[PDB]
Image (cartoon, rainbow over all chains, first blue to last red; front, side, top):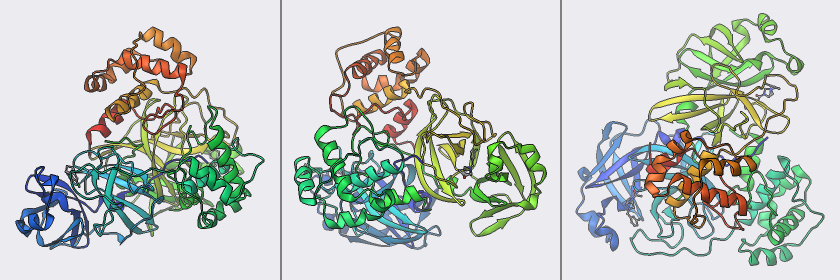
Length: 304
Length: 304
Ligand SMILES: *CC(=O)N1C[C@@H]2C[C@H]1CN2Cc1cccc(Cl)c1
Ligand SMILES: *CC(=O)N1C[C@@H]2C[C@H]1CN2Cc1cccc(Cl)c1
């Protein structure tokens, strides 16, 4: 028992982190097979970042301008290309530590682990969620760009995020591994505002089920509700609307605890209306939304 | 910017996890050099756990009774010994993935990462703190015993904890890598109560400095206090007493922010007396105590 914000073991991703330098800019790259993926803004100077024309900037760059270092050894660059907001640097050596992998574009509400890196070296691992406004609330300093978000299913790593920037509000924006930004963000040093950061309702419900499984049951009430009644309350508290797709995904948790999804929705409704009254749930004084129903099942079952 | 509960990259420890089976009991082992370390209760049956005599139980066990598997391959056991509450199984092969390592017995208040494992396979990584009552609030299911807690300084892994049991209250107890339990706990299926779980004051202060660095400054007040005045308040709220040793360790954080340690203590005092008033600090509605002053500096500086 016990419930923690748990990240995937990061070893398989640590073996893929490299340092990429172009000119005076150094960031992180992801080395999978004979390709190194990194943010295309590695070709920019601070001057270029204000209004970059990446195609024009890339013309002045040759393979030898991209310095790729894995550990203390230099990789030879034999090709380069821009795919959306990422650069793909073809190297002459396949990464011997390449795990089984996939590139996935996640939906908002989905969680993943981030291996924060600096100079191609890992510094820490933490669990994130892609917010409904397509930002992530990470912990990234200068030099962290190119750090990646991922999920692991047994031996396969699904890379879902690559860090590119910090908005002026301190929240983070990035792309999938095909270089497409999550959200409307662009890789430019221009003020870009994030939309409403709503709460991931299905995740809060999953975490309430996790709390029941672990013994924290004080919040359970004698009430039920309907999807339409619950959503009227959810809209008011800037919670994402709950759909029957979300109810379906909470089914195994509902079955394990014997608490119907709509009864858990009614407990959530009263928690929103009355607050916690100075109480905690799983050692938290607020409703946690960065655990999916899959995360709860995984942690409560011990999937390795 | 941004502040997260961050764990160390777990790769160096993942390469050390093995599965140990003795009879019908399977748990995790830590393979460093030619020795596999695991909880001695691997020799117990559920019947034995009630009142085990480990010396007597160990007499009926030979090297061939300890099955050690690393990945899909079996390690040959050429010696065994009990050191306090851990068994050391000498194998004929040195672990090729043995990182540079040390065994450290941590003090309460110190944080570490746990690589939760099942059947010698890693399932997740999270950040913990050794509570002042010598328990940890982990996430451990049956089969997780033998999972270890650690810290990493550049390339050296300092193993500080090995998981042994869950108290009837759902909190966790274990040993250092020499087999000595943290706290008064014994490896026996008997009700053992934990003492008062006080708050790690120096850690809360460190996290308040982290909050100031990251822009959350609403809690800062126009007040100061003394160590004796603060401790009168800390004693009342079951917070650990703050010493000049703790003030000394907060010095770099005090210097970076320009906020004297005693002024931060006065902000903490008002937070304890008035509560958060429905507000948050670093996305938390309670005062976080599982970040040491070293963790805050490390994360706010990007140590890899
Ligand atoms: C995170 C990282 O490594 N970098 C590279 C430079 C400094 C920091 C951010 N990068 C500049 C930048 C500004 C605005 C937008 C984007 Cl995409 C990048
Ligand atoms: C965590 C783990 O792998 N185990 C082994 C068995 C089941 C679970 C706990 N172990 C029994 C036990 C009961 C009381 C105290 C201790 Cl030290 C162990």
